[PDB]
Image 1 (cartoon, each protein chain N blue to C red):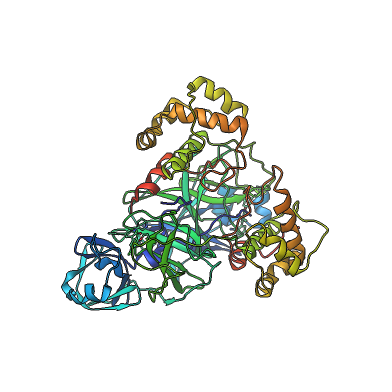
Image 2: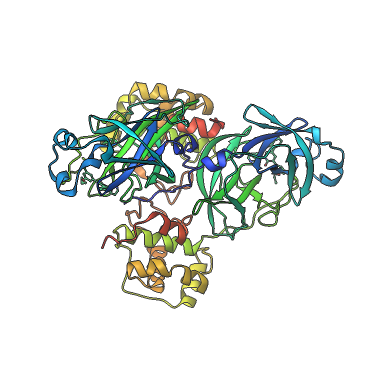
Length: 306
Length: 305
Ligand SMILES: CCCOc1cc(Cl)cc(-c2cc(-c3ccccc3C#N)cn(-c3cccnc3)c2=O)c1
Ligand SMILES: CCCOc1cc(Cl)cc(-c2cc(-c3ccccc3C#N)cn(-c3cccnc3)c2=O)c1
């Protein structure tokens, strides 16, 4: 029993974190095999930020303008290349701590663990979701660029996020590990703003199923809804459209609880209309949308508390 | 910017988790130096747990009755003994990944990170607090006994919790690493209940300071109060008393924000008496009480390990 924002154990990723310095700019890198990955804005200067020409900035660098430090050991850079918004530094030693890993670009609504790091050293670990507007609501201070997000289903690390920027609203933007930004953002300090964000509907339904699995049914009702009518209502509360894909993805939780997906949709409609009237759901007074269906099956018992 | 419930990096503890099997029972153990630590109820059958005599049960077991697995490697048990509710299994090899560590017993209100483990294999990490009623609101399934809670204080892992039981209400109870239970619980399979819980006042104040650091400040007001008057209000709303020691512990956050503790106390008093509007604080509609003052400092300052 219980239900918390549960991150993956971070040790497999801690063993990959290094410090990268170019000029007076220092941030984090990710050391996998004999390559160190980091944001390309490590090569920018304080004046370079509005409209940097990264190709022109990079050709002026030699391998030895990059200082990479793994703990108290300096790594020797023997090559460098730019891939989209990520810099790839080839080093003379493979990381002996490299886990099994892959790179995956995730969809809005997917969740992942973030290992926040400063000067190549880890500070803390927490769960995040890719918002519908392609930002993440992280906890990052100056020096955190190069921190990564990941999942570790099975024993394989799936790297999905590298942190590049904090936006004026206080949310965060970054890339996959191929250097392609999530969303419309670009790595320069020009005015940019994330779109209006929405609530991840499939995730709220997953979390309501978690509540039922753990023994709570007070919010259910005797009604149902069509998918079309549910989306018509949900849209008025700034919820994302629920698709047939999402209904399919919720199938396992529906099967375990005996609650048809569209019947849980009717419960959500009523919660949006009524509020919680002093009650809570899994400890929250607001509807939670950063647990995916997969996250719920990962954490909850396979046996409903009936 | 931003503020999240944040756990310590778990790598130093991951290297310490092992699987312990006795008879048909498997759970987790903590491997430090040449000793594995786990709950003593590992030696019970289900009927044993109904009313266990642990010293008598342990007498009937030898070293080879304990099967200890570190990953794929089998560890050779060379001794065994109990300390309070914890079994100590001496093994023939010291853990080469043993971090600098110590054993600490925490006070209610203190937070810690939990590394939830199954079959000796870490599966997740999350942040908990020791509740005033000495339970923790964890997230644990069968097989999780022996998972540990910890803080990292500079270079040193301070282990403070080992998981033993889930209570009927779904909260959790465990011991320090010397086997002393937190709370009025015993390791026997029987109906046990925690007392009515209360809210951790100093932690709610720390989180209001975190909200002001992050620019969320609608709840500040012109009023101040006294420690005595505030404690009358805390008692009425089932909040823990606020001591002068708590005021001093909030010192650094009061210094970072410039807002005196008794100033903030008048804000919290008005929130307790009137609620929020339809308003939130740091995204929450409830007053959060599982961030300590030091938790707020370390997250907002970027302290590393
Ligand atoms: C769109 C508005 C912001 O546009 C940009 C554009 C670019 Cl190219 C980079 C940054 C950025 C740089 C830097 C930075 C700078 C110098 C040395 C080191 C670093 C680092 N570490 C930090 N942080 C930051 C701060 C706080 C929380 N998280 C990220 C940035 O957002 C910001
Ligand atoms: C107060 C009512 C419960 O009284 C007890 C007393 C004692 Cl001595 C132990 C337990 C207990 C045992 C066991 C257990 C048993 C056999 C083999 C392995 C394990 C394990 N792992 C699991 N879990 C448990 C389950 C879910 C979440 N977290 C903990 C217990 O609470 C429960």
